[PDB]
Image (cartoon, rainbow over all chains, first blue to last red; front, side, top):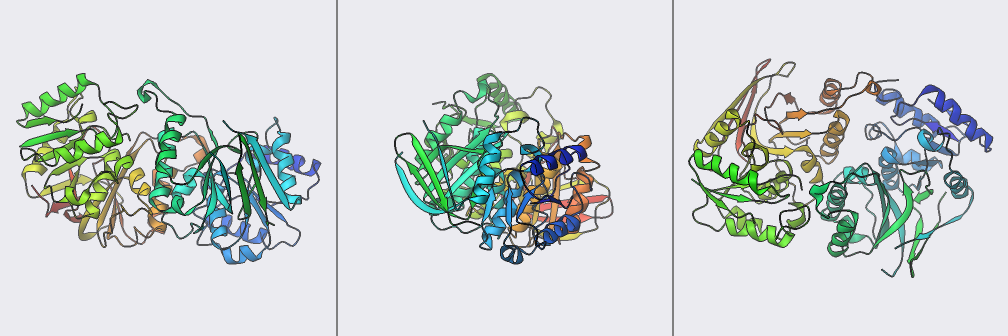
Length: 285
Length: 291
């Protein structure tokens, strides 16, 4: 387990506290962790990820914080060597951009937890931590939840933070996934800002090529009387009419306490029967 | 001349609109109010808002078309006929979310104007003479020159097609067929409620997509109402601007008096701009746009 910092300033004592959480659950910890909001400069934050991908005693590379700064670390990095590194990169939020360029180079990543929140907090979630070690040590996963259409598609699983996905639009770092399953999560946004970013990927022609769209934990909004009925249900009804692909909700992944580790790059199996959803992902390192 | 009021995004209370029409009357213009139907957050449904744009562009007594609000246009890009709008000969003005409408017009070869709207430029009681006089001048004069004072800017002397608008709406256009393919132009951006890291992020999308590499110069408008903290550790607009100029290959010029501010200028999107910076003294002449 390697703890790199793509671009996040974290309190000094909380990281040392999260180290004990990693060691008390059986994991060899190797930390590679300042400049303004970032844990280092662009070249140093680029080098720490490169050196972490070369240490033989390293299997899992977990990001430190997912604020902003990983897009700066795209040209100074060699994602071709990162694909051959055989490492297990996990993370979310800003770190989603790094996992797209990996999938752009045919490398499977994991969209799961990070050290900033899922390991430094005193309100540890057994759901999040157990699903993490399960995805790391099991050849298959199964994501079942309770949902409030009939789908049964199979394709390449990919996705991540919605703001980062809208940020990847038009850039060479966006994976050209043909007929896959796309999941999205975000926080502190608005249903109209969520609909706006989803229309960017639809106008760009990405949503038309996919075979299913999954909605994750879109957390913590703020509505007013000016909305006049516009909410998450108003968008979802309008989005299911605009999009030609099915839209399934209830994915337990986002900026929440409870989250699952989603392999970005594996072969998924989305199923909607009668309110019981099930997502089986296979073939991932 | 004649003007038409359209609501491409949100709605405005009827009390404020009637006061805004009186201002356009006092300044000597014939108002044609197409705003009525009201649908949730928007002033009308997507099909009704689309029909109101096609109808105002066909009225022979209308010459200028102004947008009501700019708080979310994208929902009806396919309902509109921008080939019909480019031939309509109307002078569309607006900003904020209306930048989406102006990029598709420029994609078809139509010159629009990034300027004021009914929202907070004609409904406010603290009316701005700078905004209203610059707006009336661009509509009635073939040339507009903008001069401002901004320090630490490079000495440039470029000339190209002026285009751009809201930074969030432009980064939203990345990857979409509605993004204009301006080669060697002068791009300007502005935004509000955005931390400088959100500004650098959307600017990186325009750089990674290859848009900034083709332009001749990048002009920064007003980026107001920030919220920095101690966790920035010295990060602000200056630290972002210095990192942007080190990353970008084109010169970045700041100080453009345009944005969601009381005082703003009317910038003809699609015109022929002449950018000149003389170590603090910056001048922007604009031409080749319909009057």
